[PDB]
Length: 109
Image (cartoon, rainbow, N blue to C red):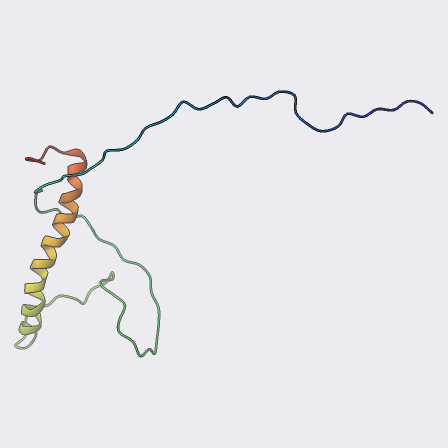
Protein backbone atom coordinates (compact mmCIF):
# COMPACT_ATOMS: atom_id res chain seq x y z
CA UNK A 1 0.00 0.00 0.00
CA UNK A 2 1.80 3.09 -1.30
CA UNK A 3 1.99 5.68 -4.08
CA UNK A 4 -0.83 8.17 -3.54
CA UNK A 5 -1.70 11.86 -3.48
CA UNK A 6 -4.36 14.55 -3.14
CA UNK A 7 -4.37 18.04 -4.66
CA UNK A 8 -7.85 19.42 -4.06
CA UNK A 9 -9.67 22.56 -5.15
CA UNK A 10 -9.30 26.18 -4.07
CA UNK A 11 -7.31 29.36 -4.69
CA UNK A 12 -3.75 30.59 -4.14
CA UNK A 13 -4.04 34.31 -3.43
CA UNK A 14 -5.77 36.40 -6.09
CA UNK A 15 -6.44 40.13 -5.71
CA UNK A 16 -9.46 42.44 -5.63
CA UNK A 17 -8.51 45.54 -3.64
CA UNK A 18 -11.00 48.24 -2.63
CA UNK A 19 -12.73 50.92 -4.74
CA UNK A 20 -11.97 54.65 -4.79
CA UNK A 21 -15.41 56.26 -4.62
CA UNK A 22 -17.05 57.93 -7.62
CA UNK A 23 -19.17 60.85 -8.81
CA UNK A 24 -21.67 61.61 -11.57
CA UNK A 25 -24.51 64.13 -11.75
CA UNK A 26 -25.64 67.54 -13.01
CA UNK A 27 -27.03 67.40 -16.55
CA UNK A 28 -29.29 69.36 -18.89
CA UNK A 29 -29.97 70.37 -22.48
CA UNK A 30 -31.40 73.89 -22.63
CA UNK A 31 -31.60 73.96 -26.43
CA UNK A 32 -33.25 76.81 -28.34
CA UNK A 33 -34.50 78.03 -31.71
CA UNK A 34 -32.97 76.15 -34.64
CA UNK A 35 -32.67 76.59 -38.40
CA UNK A 36 -35.19 75.59 -41.07
CA UNK A 37 -35.38 73.40 -44.17
CA UNK A 38 -33.64 70.04 -44.54
CA UNK A 39 -35.23 67.42 -46.78
CA UNK A 40 -33.17 64.35 -45.86
CA UNK A 41 -35.52 61.79 -44.31
CA UNK A 42 -37.07 59.11 -46.50
CA UNK A 43 -37.75 55.41 -46.01
CA UNK A 44 -40.38 52.72 -45.45
CA UNK A 45 -40.92 49.31 -43.86
CA UNK A 46 -42.53 46.11 -45.19
CA UNK A 47 -46.12 45.04 -44.48
CA UNK A 48 -48.78 42.52 -45.50
CA UNK A 49 -52.39 41.80 -44.55
CA UNK A 50 -55.83 41.08 -46.02
CA UNK A 51 -59.43 40.99 -44.83
CA UNK A 52 -59.53 42.98 -41.60
CA UNK A 53 -62.18 44.88 -39.64
CA UNK A 54 -59.79 47.47 -38.20
CA UNK A 55 -58.34 50.85 -39.11
CA UNK A 56 -55.27 51.13 -41.34
CA UNK A 57 -51.50 50.68 -41.24
CA UNK A 58 -49.47 52.66 -43.78
CA UNK A 59 -47.93 56.04 -44.58
CA UNK A 60 -45.83 56.10 -47.75
CA UNK A 61 -44.25 53.41 -49.94
CA UNK A 62 -41.93 53.38 -52.95
CA UNK A 63 -43.75 53.62 -56.27
CA UNK A 64 -45.89 56.21 -58.04
CA UNK A 65 -49.52 57.20 -57.45
CA UNK A 66 -49.77 59.61 -54.52
CA UNK A 67 -50.00 63.37 -55.07
CA UNK A 68 -52.13 65.02 -57.75
CA UNK A 69 -53.40 68.30 -59.18
CA UNK A 70 -55.41 68.29 -62.40
CA UNK A 71 -59.12 67.53 -62.20
CA UNK A 72 -62.23 69.43 -61.15
CA UNK A 73 -62.65 67.24 -58.06
CA UNK A 74 -59.23 66.23 -56.76
CA UNK A 75 -58.61 69.94 -56.21
CA UNK A 76 -60.49 69.71 -52.91
CA UNK A 77 -58.74 66.55 -51.71
CA UNK A 78 -55.44 68.33 -52.36
CA UNK A 79 -56.44 71.53 -50.57
CA UNK A 80 -57.28 69.40 -47.53
CA UNK A 81 -53.92 67.64 -47.30
CA UNK A 82 -52.16 70.86 -48.31
CA UNK A 83 -53.01 72.79 -45.16
CA UNK A 84 -51.91 69.73 -43.21
CA UNK A 85 -48.66 69.39 -45.16
CA UNK A 86 -47.59 72.76 -43.76
CA UNK A 87 -48.10 72.16 -40.04
CA UNK A 88 -46.62 68.69 -40.52
CA UNK A 89 -43.55 70.06 -42.29
CA UNK A 90 -42.67 72.39 -39.42
CA UNK A 91 -42.86 69.31 -37.19
CA UNK A 92 -40.22 67.44 -39.19
CA UNK A 93 -38.01 70.53 -39.33
CA UNK A 94 -37.91 71.08 -35.57
CA UNK A 95 -36.79 67.46 -35.35
CA UNK A 96 -34.00 67.47 -37.94
CA UNK A 97 -32.85 71.04 -37.30
CA UNK A 98 -33.21 70.33 -33.59
CA UNK A 99 -30.60 67.58 -33.81
CA UNK A 100 -28.18 70.01 -35.45
CA UNK A 101 -27.40 71.53 -32.06
CA UNK A 102 -25.39 68.39 -31.40
CA UNK A 103 -22.62 69.99 -33.44
CA UNK A 104 -23.42 73.64 -34.14
CA UNK A 105 -23.28 77.16 -32.70
CA UNK A 106 -26.86 78.50 -32.53
CA UNK A 107 -27.99 81.75 -30.91
CA UNK A 108 -28.52 81.63 -27.14
CA UNK A 109 -29.24 78.44 -25.20
